[PDB]
Image 1 (tube, rainbow, N blue to C red):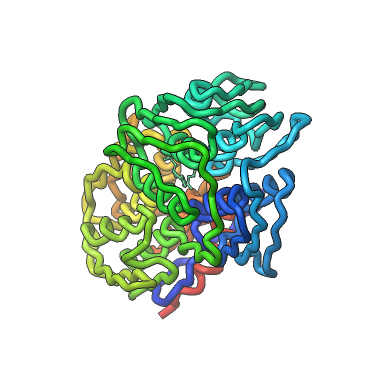
Image 2: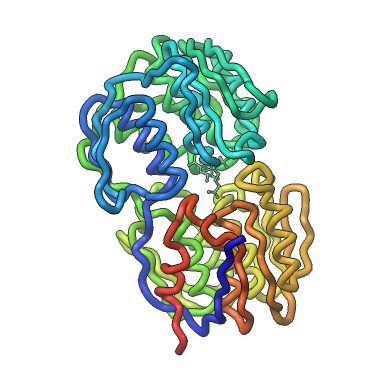
Length: 427
Ligand SMILES: O=C(O)C1=C[C@@H](OP(=O)(O)O)[C@@H](O)[C@H](O)C1
Ligand SMILES: O=C(O)C[NH2+]CP(=O)(O)O
């Protein structure tokens, strides 16, 4: 078991140029692969989740080149649905953005492809998406546990009236939205009830428009899509910096700054996680917005009680920042933390208690009462990049912290610790 120990950080201050957005990166790669023409993506994220998408495109026969640092990608569009036969197996790690989107996209036309991944991915639900794709005509077989990957996709999605449950993941709807335009018939996607992680749907529609396709969004309850469309290369496209990755650095300033500025995202960003800055402001920090930056300056830090359904990923950062806030913090409406890289409600409550907090692990919320002083702990990370990054913040105190399996940050941010060190100051 590898581990790293972080020494106490007296103050943070500086500027971080963000790694590319994982969410934008994987959508842009799939759309570029489906489109006609050559797309040049810049500021693409180099991380496990994107690498699995790149490897999948390679296996499907898509041609592309990568720059030395893997952040510039020149993709030769396929000019239509991707294809492979012979039950070709695509390994997708634990990348939901790739598993869900490809599960839908590869249902176009005929194909015989198997999508699989790491053990945890075989425990992450996908039944809501499979149910919808089947209503649209797709043939899909669960090779192991019903409602979970691995899936054998044999094609047939033609369109029509499709219902989809949006209560567990917005990724199912996102997958359907990117796929439907290329189906032969028109598609009407009806949301069954609640829709979680709504801002990610806006990211999807934004990317689709960039690639030449628009649809009719009827108050996020029903989406009307015309079939027979084609995606078109946007030429050169700049991938936004990752707003979720930015959360750690902005929170670090709110706790121990100083002023920390992140570049690559700004007031015009399409990512819902830029709203994380709003939460820090509500807690007492000062936020500055620019065209291509967001900065946070230390003010004070007070506990909050908020519904975090709109920023589920960045919300984890508030759970450890809460260790430094005055009062008890409550994060609500975050049930799907349970079905992601690990069951995050169980994991965050367990590790937070190890450093001294009193924590109520609710079914779909977490209540955190900070200790008068933190203690040292060896933090388990559950193969979850964000557990490692969130707990790195414990070092902005008088105690060091040991993080197990620090390389798990590579899912979305391989260089995380060196970047945190960049803004860590001794004086
Ligand atoms: O579509 C996307 O890019 C994502 C949507 C979210 O998932 P859910 O919709 O399941 O909350 C988020 O947690 C994930 O990291 C990325
Ligand atoms: O990035 C996160 O915090 C959660 N990601 C879930 P996935 O992208 O694997 O579906």
